[PDB]
Image (cartoon, rainbow over all chains, first blue to last red; front, top):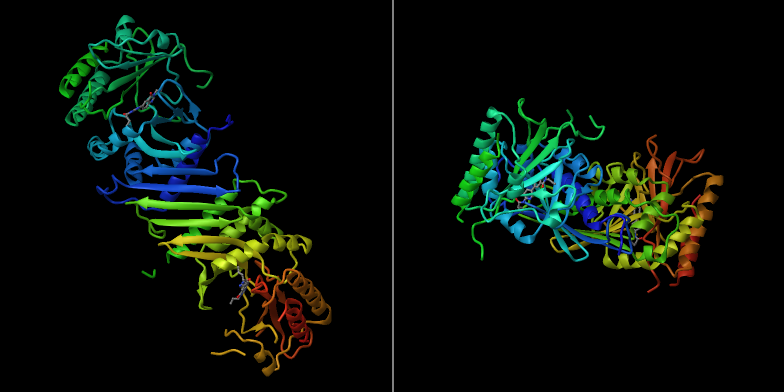
Amino acid sequence: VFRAADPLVGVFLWGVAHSINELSQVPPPVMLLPDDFKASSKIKVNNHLFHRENLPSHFKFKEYCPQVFRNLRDRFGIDDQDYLVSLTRNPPSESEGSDGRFLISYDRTLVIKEVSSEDIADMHSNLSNYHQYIVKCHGNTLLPQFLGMYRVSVDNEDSYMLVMRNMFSHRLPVHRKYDLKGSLVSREASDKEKVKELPTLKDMDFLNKNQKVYIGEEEKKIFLEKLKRDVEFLVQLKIMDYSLLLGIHDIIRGSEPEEESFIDVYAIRSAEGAPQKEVYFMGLIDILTQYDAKKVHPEQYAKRFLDFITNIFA
Amino acid sequence: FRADPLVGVFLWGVAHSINELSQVPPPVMLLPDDFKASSKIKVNNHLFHRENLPSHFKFKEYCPQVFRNLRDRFGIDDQDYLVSLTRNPPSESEGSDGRFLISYDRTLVIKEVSSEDIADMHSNLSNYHQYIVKCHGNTLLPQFLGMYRVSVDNEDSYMLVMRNMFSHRLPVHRKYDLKGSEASDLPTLKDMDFLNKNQKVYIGEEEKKIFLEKLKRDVEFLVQLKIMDYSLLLGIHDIIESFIDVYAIRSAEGAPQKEVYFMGLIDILTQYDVHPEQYAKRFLDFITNIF
Ligand SMILES: CCCCC(=O)Nc1ccc(-c2ccc3ncn(CCC)c(=O)c3c2)cn1
Ligand SMILES: CCCCC(=O)Nc1ccc(-c2ccc3ncn(CCC)c(=O)c3c2)cn1
């Protein structure tokens, strides 16, 4: 059943418009109540002998905790209308690498990742904790910015979408990619992964390449003290198995002929004495994983993580 | 409890439909499927709260392509239809046994109807639609512009939106429901009080026949469908630029009073189950008899 447009994205793009447009009529609550953290807005469409081109005739769309995620976007500095333009003005571009879908907004500021149903449950188990941490740090963090969480039902099949700020650059393309855990049971990018154009390298590949990150001592201090706070928050929640996403843009290799419009929140320029002029992009990914696993405590995972990351700097 | 969700949902559904319909190109020709089609939407929010709309409702539009085409053939743009119903709440009328709302514009009417009138509309929607294209929309019959079903707190109410037959600016002072064969206590006069009050309409020779020729055409379209028990709604405004009252006929030159008459057929679609062509025969001669 080849289609030119994927109905899963079309229904998602429809539902984001509908969600935000109805949200424009609902005044923001003065304080989020514990009921807002179990709330949801669903809507089910049933057209009969009335066909549309972009959307299927039978679909559902649900938004998880609208008031919570609306408040989160605000605290992260994103106007709801800017969120809408960025996701819907033009179709997002598809990216490969992750399990299911992984979309990038047309302005390359937002990311939309397909997650599982247990991931949706893990977010609810800690949305209140995550929100209270965004309040406390005023949104200045290395954790991902969870901006919206949605369920898209099409052809009697539910997909779960999660929107976030893009940790990479809206305009500077990433030339080298790592995912760093600091672990012992060592991590190499597979042969299958390594022959791609942009392979996600891991701890051992980082070391094998003599990779170092040159940012200068003040930025190093701010980044490590931030990383330390964020990790302690996860440790308190008994979380482990998270990663630092590290991207590297080669400056002299440049972008395409495309050279103020947006701020790359997770970017740090290289130090003035660096051997290479580059831009780094760093963020924690795959948080929200509890220690309970059916065959390392969160405190030990963290200490090892922080010590590894501390030494990637030079 | 009475501060109203039925109106609040209905107006939410109309904006939602006209927004959806702006993204579906209007067809040039209709299919038999379009006369059995429908668009249904169900909202269910959980610990989410909004002012106007309740937490749970349904909105169903009947044959969206047909009525959209009928609004086109009646000279109504969809956006002007949307502004008309929703930009300010419709004022209600206490013509009871169901709700009866008039747009802020006074250009359109929203009448609550039964589940069998919905069945009656579907049995003849195509017959009605093709009569409209042949007369190029120049009829005394009502202009059915849209038909929806709203569900709130597990009760289904059916809404039919028609063009307003009365004026959008000039109020009606006398109102008749003319049939042929008296009213118990603007009141709705029945037929005897036309006579008793020596009421007569003066509209001019040339315009009287154009109305009567179309009345014969319209009625002759109903009798071919075994329709009876229709009425001629006659509104009357003693004369003591934005829109048009297309059922208004101006004061005749040299009349006792210079006035404006609003006349068009209502409560059609009642099928025989006194004969249709007899019922015709009596009504037509009755209404032909005012000069
Ligand atoms: C419901 C709980 C979910 C658990 C959970 O924390 N997952 C999680 C968290 C964050 C990300 C993420 C965010 C931004 C990103 N920007 C760029 N790139 C680079 C693209 C090549 C990313 O990969 C990226 C990945 C992915 N997954
Ligand atoms: C689906 C229903 C089948 C039966 C059926 O044809 N009903 C039916 C048909 C037409 C009307 C109608 C139309 C326009 C009108 N304009 C003004 N005013 C004046 C308001 C004071 C009206 O009353 C009016 C009433 C009412 N009912």
